[PDB]
Length: 13
Image (cartoon, rainbow, N blue to C red):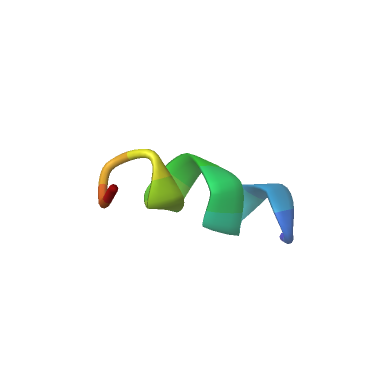
């Protein structure tokens, strides 16, 4: 679930 880190990242920075 790598793409999951990219979608959770948008919520961060």
